[PDB]
Structures are given as structure tokens and as C-alpha cells.
Amino acid sequence: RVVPSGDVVRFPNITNLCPFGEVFNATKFPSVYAWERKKISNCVADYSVLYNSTFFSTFKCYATKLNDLCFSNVYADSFVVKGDDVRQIAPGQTGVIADYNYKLPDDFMGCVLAWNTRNIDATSTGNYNYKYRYLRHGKLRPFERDISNVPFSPDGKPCTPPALNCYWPLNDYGFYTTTGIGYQPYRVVVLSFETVCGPKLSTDLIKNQCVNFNFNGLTGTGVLTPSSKRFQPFQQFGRDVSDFTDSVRDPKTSEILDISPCAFGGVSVITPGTNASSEVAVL
Amino acid sequence: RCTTFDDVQAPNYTQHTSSMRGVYYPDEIFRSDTLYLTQDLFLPFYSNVTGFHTINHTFGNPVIPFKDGIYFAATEKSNVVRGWVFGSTMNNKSQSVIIINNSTNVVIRACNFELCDNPFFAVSKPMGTQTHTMIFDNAFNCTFEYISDAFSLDVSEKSGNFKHLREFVFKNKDGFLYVYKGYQPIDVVRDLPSGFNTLKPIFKLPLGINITNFRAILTAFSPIWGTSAAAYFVGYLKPTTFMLKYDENGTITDAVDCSQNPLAELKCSVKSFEIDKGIYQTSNF
Ligand SMILES: *[C@@H]1O[C@H](CO)[C@@H](O[C@@H]2O[C@H](CO)[C@@H](O[C@@H]3O[C@H](CO)[C@@H](O)[C@H](O)[C@@H]3O)[C@H](O)[C@H]2NC(C)=O)[C@H](O)[C@H]1NC(C)=O
Ligand SMILES: *[C@@H]1O[C@H](CO)[C@@H](O[C@@H]2O[C@H](CO)[C@@H](O)[C@H](O)[C@H]2NC(C)=O)[C@H](O)[C@H]1NC(C)=O
Ligand SMILES: *[C@@H]1O[C@H](CO)[C@@H](O[C@@H]2O[C@H](CO)[C@@H](O)[C@H](O)[C@H]2NC(C)=O)[C@H](O)[C@H]1NC(C)=O
Ligand SMILES: *[C@@H]1O[C@H](CO)[C@@H](O[C@@H]2O[C@H](CO)[C@@H](O)[C@H](O)[C@H]2NC(C)=O)[C@H](O)[C@H]1NC(C)=O
Ligand SMILES: *[C@@H]1O[C@H](CO)[C@@H](O)[C@H](O)[C@H]1NC(C)=O
């Protein structure tokens, strides 16, 4: 048998791209206790508009899910962080975000794209519409939000602030434009895998070789060459007089390839005998 | 606005001969220079077709049973049916499907519909423009919405004989409605024109409902909602075996029912259409 060498994976033209310019570059994001459940479904969440950019500080995935995004109905959860809260957008990492604002697990998450919005979110005196929680009666569980400005009391007494043992849970992030890096705002989107998928890995038609392949639904080894088989417009691929697949319309460019077996066959050895020679000719 | 037909007259139930129609391309696979026995839902040959003629004020469009699949065929000049209502009870109790042609495009929704008890296509008859699809007023819990390409549709009282013979195949298959279409250019006046004809696939429709019945929607041809002369036809898809012959082009030229007579099952057996004189062992009983 002749061992194949080569890989022809072709997919169609990619279906509906997710609006990353209007979800992961949108104009209206909340704080971190109250992530915006941006429902995107039946889409291609490819990160391709954003992974090749210079906006983003983290690229932290748990935008490498440009490779490996294929999940359920994902709500493209979006939010605005403190500069010191940028690092805490991760599984675990028991700081301000995970304890009180939004806890993140280590299974159903995508990529952290944290991009600079100093001249979009912050002012010279402070954007005081964005708040973080630093105290709550109990830490959070994963993918839970808490929008309530709860009249906090650290020992269980009924609380009407600013009375005795009464704090406000929501502290302002303090988004300046004339501060250091640690108190700059990043608009961030993190995927919650609650259906979107990734882009299409597509490559060459290495014709007239024993290669592997994987078309849009058809695998195996073969030899690829164009054909004269007049497919109809509704036709995926072709079969022979018997029931094996022998021809396929290319899912991206509609070329009608032929699919032949890779190669094999028998071997004879022709010999005059050990008493006459020790060379042979194989067949 | 849901209104009904007013001058509703008695139905026809005319029997027809289904001679050589209802054959279609079941898969999306190309095969050629071959001969292929397979089993699916099909029209039995020479079977009975109930015909619904539209004579002067016969509004012969009740809720018609479906059960697995149906055949719509219609000798048309004015295309008096442009709509079907799929579902079980069709009303806004369960999810139902409307597929209609509003003379601009084919608009398709699968929702809980406030259906008219007699829905229709509001058309000025001697002017020939469809004004409204008086079918549903409100839609609820919508699951799929489709709009076809925009096209100009002849909706007037066409004179002469019927020039268009569409063939339709509708299949509820695992959440999916499959809609197939064939066509014969015709010039006919009477019962049901015989002839071999094929269909092709257009639609895979994830509507996702129960469809036990369907409702035929006539076009109201009124100058009070009225008629013009047409007829349309109802057949049944049944799970039997056909053997089908493909040319070099992969086009169906010829196929054969297995269930007609012992001649036909013999042809299904030896995989040929030409059988020598002799005696042939066939299936036991
Ligand atoms: C599959 O479909 C094609 C249609 O594209 C069929 O090919 C056509 O066949 C006809 C007759 O079989 C050809 O007509 C011939 O034309 C020449 C000159 O054009 C004329 O001298 C002959 O007397 C005859 O009329 C036609 O040209 C041909 N088309 C092409 C593009 O070759 C084909 O026959 C179909 N396959 C089968 C098995 O029927
Ligand atoms: C998938 O996309 C490719 C390119 O993005 C399409 O290739 C074009 O095809 C049309 C006709 O189908 C040609 O006129 C163009 O010249 C092709 N593009 C180039 C750059 O040469 C291809 O058609 C698309 N697939 C489908 C099924 O439409
Ligand atoms: C291989 O062939 C040689 C012949 O070239 C054989 O050797 C001779 O065999 C004959 C009879 O078979 C004797 O009369 C000779 O005396 C042998 N000559 C020698 C030099 O041995 C040999 O026996 C053959 N061997 C086999 C295993 O077939
Ligand atoms: C279509 O239905 C008609 C009746 O509605 C069938 O015709 C009768 O069938 C019975 C039983 O087979 C016979 O005894 C009668 O002689 C038939 N009468 C006529 C006028 O044909 C008919 O067989 C049905 N079609 C098919 C293909 O079975
Ligand atoms: C018709 O079939 C018979 C089978 O016995 C055969 O002998 C005969 O040659 C056929 N007819 C022609 C014109 O060949």
C-alpha cells in the first residue's frame, strides 16, 4: 500500500460572521457586576476582526479561540474594568471581579479582549458611572451577576446607610484620563458558553497525489483530479455505479473533482531459484 | 383582517388517474449510467387523485389531511393557489406554518397564527394586483421567518387555457419541510394530463412542528370574494420501493413502481426494463 502524504481540507465560504465591530467594539457597555448578555447564535465567532489588531491588552483565552470556538448559544458578555482589574478577568483569581462582581470558571469561557478606551470611557475628572463591588454577604458563584446596590452590613444587622456598621458596596473605579495605567478603563468582552462556532480551516487542492482529505462532510484517502461529471446545482457529491463515493463538488469553489483510490495491489517475486541466482525482479 | 369567503359552494372530490407523475430526486447525490433500487415515500402509479376544481363559486379549499406528505399539482393560468397552511390545528394554539406568495415574493413564517377561518388572497379580478394576504392578522412565538426574492407575479383572470402545470412535493421529515418543484408547459382543459415528469429540491425548512393537516389557500378573484376557473390536486406519498434509471447526465428518464403488477416487481427483481421470455422465480409469499 502507498501511504498518503498531504491534507486537503476545504470548507465553504464561511457563514455569517459575528458582529465583532458592533459587539466587541460596541458603544455601550456596563460595569463588571452586571455583564451585558449579548446573545449571539447561529453565527461564526471567529475573533478575526480583533485578533489582528493593536487595541487589546490580554488576548487571554481559557484570541486563540480563533482556532477553537465551537460551542452553544454564547452570550457575548461585555463589561468595563479597572486597569488593575484587567488581570483578574480569568478563571479563579480571587480579587474584586471574581469575588463580588462576576466569578469566572475554568471550563466554559472564551477569550478576554480588553482594549483601551481612555478617550471613550474616562474623563479628566473621573467617569463615576462605572462602579465595582468590594463587599457582599458572601462571595459569588460562577456566571452570576449582582446589580443590586445592597445596603451592606458586615454582621447581619438591618442597615440604612450612613448609620452604624453600614457601607456602600459599589465603589467607583475612578476612570481618569490623567492617571497612571492602573486606573485606566478597558472595555472588555468575555464569552459565556451558554450557537456560534469558529471560522473555516481551508487549504490547497493538491491534485494527482495520494493524500488524506476532509471536505465538507467527506473524509478518507484519495487522488484528486477534475472531472466532466455534470453535477446538478443541488448535488453535494457523486457515487459510482456501486455505492462508494468517487466524485465531489468542491464546497468552496464548486470544482467537480474525481476521487480515486490511493493505490495498492499485489506483489509477485520472480526467481530462477537459489541454486542459480540471488537477484530477483519484483512485479 | 380575517374575513371568510361568502359564496362558498359544495366541494368536488373528483377522482383522477395519477399516471406517471410524482417522481423526484430524493438525495443530493449524483449518480449516472446506472439503475438504482430504493425505498422512500412516493406516489403510487395510476392511483386515485382527488381533484378540486374551481367552478363559478366553488371554494373547494378545506383543511386537507397530510399525514406524511402530499402532492400538490395544478393546471394553472391565474395561479389561484399561492398558499398553504401547515400544522395540526393551524390556529394560535400550537405552532403552525404559513407559506404564501403575496405577488411580490414568497413569505414564510412558522408562528402561532390568528388564522382566518377561511383565509384567502385579496385580488381585484379584472385589474390583476394582489392587495393583501387576508390569512393571519397577528403572529406569536415565531420560530422561523423566510422571505424569498422579489418577483412580479401575474395574478389576473387569465383567459385561454391553462399554460402552467406545477408539481409540488411536501415532506415533514424530522423538523424539516422539504419542498420540491416540477413544471410542465401545458395547454389543456380537462381531467388530469398524463405524462412522465420529474421534480427537483429547493427547500430544507427547519420549521420544527407537527403537521398532520394542511389548508389550501385559494386566491380570491373578486371585482365579496370570488373565483376564476382553475383546478388543483391532492396526492399521497407512500413508503414503497422504486427502481430508477439515470442517464449519462444523471437525469431521471425512467422509473418503475414495484407494487403495480407482478410484471413490475419482476422488473424490480432482475434490475432491468427488458425481460426475456421465460419463467422467473420472484419473491415468496
Ligand atoms: C445529456 O445532455 C446533453 C445536453 O447538453 C446531450 O447532448 C446533446 O445531444 C444531442 C443529441 O443527442 C446533440 O445534438 C446533436 O448536435 C449535432 C451538432 O450540434 C448534430 O449534428 C446532431 O445531429 C445532433 O442533433 C447535442 O449537440 C448534444 N449537446 C452537447 C453539448 O453535446 C446528451 O445527449 C445528454 N445525454 C444523454 C445520454 O442523452
Ligand atoms: C466562495 O468565495 C469565492 C471567493 O471569495 C468565490 O469565488 C468567486 O467565484 C465567482 C463565481 O462563482 C467568480 O466570478 C470570482 O472570480 C471568484 N472569485 C475570485 C477572487 O476569483 C466563490 O464563488 C464562492 N463560492 C460560492 C459557492 O459562491
Ligand atoms: C545446484 O546445482 C548444482 C549444479 O550446478 C548441483 O551440483 C552438482 O549436482 C550434480 C547432481 O545433482 C553432481 O553430479 C555434481 O557433482 C554437483 N556439483 C557440485 C559442485 O556440487 C547442486 O547439487 C545443486 N544443489 C541443489 C540444492 O539443488
Ligand atoms: C380509485 O377508487 C375507485 C373507487 O373510488 C376504485 O374503483 C373501484 O375499485 C373497486 C375495488 O378495487 C372495484 O370493485 C370497482 O370495480 C372499481 N370501480 C371503478 C369505477 O373503477 C379504483 O380501483 C381506485 N384506483 C385504484 C388504482 O385502485
Ligand atoms: C422480441 O423478443 C423475442 C424473445 O423471444 C426475440 O426472439 C425477438 O428477436 C425480439 N424481437 C426482435 C425484433 O428482435
Image (cartoon, coloured by chain):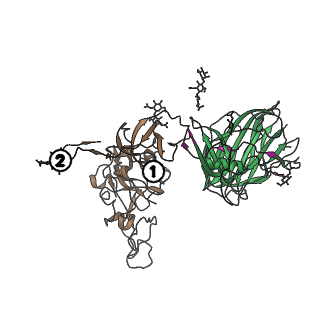
Q: Residue A256 versus residue B66: which sits nearer the camera?
A: A256
- Span highlighted in magenta in the image: B16-34
User: Residue A275, labelled with which disc?
Assistant: 2
Q: Is residue B237 above or below residue B227?
A: below
Q: In screen coordinates, is A212 left or right of B205?
A: left
Quarter of the view holding residue A104: bottom left
Q: Amino acid at mark 1?
A: Lys
Q: Is mark 1 within 8 Å of ligand 2?
A: no
Q: Is mark 2 within 8 Å of ligand 3?
A: yes
Q: Amino acid at mark 2?
A: Asn
Q: Residue at x 48, y 49 (%)?
A: A43
Q: Position of residue B264 (x, y in %)?
A: 69, 48
Colour of chain A in the rendered structure image: brown
Quarter of the image that includes the C terminus of chain A = top left
Q: In screen coordinates, is B214 left or right of A236?
A: right
What is the letter of the green chain? B
Residue that carries the numbered disc 1 in the rendered image: A28
From mark 1 to mark 2, how far is it between C-alphas?
Answer: 91 Å
Q: Residue A119 versus residue A18: which sits nearer the camera?
A: A18
Classify mark 1: helix, strand or loop.
Answer: loop
- Asked whether B30 falls inside the magenta stretch, the response is yes
Q: Position of residue A235 (x, y in %)?
A: 54, 41
Q: Is residue B92 above or below residue B222?
A: below
- Sort mark 1 into few (<14), some (14-19) or many (20+) by Cα contacts within 10 Å: few
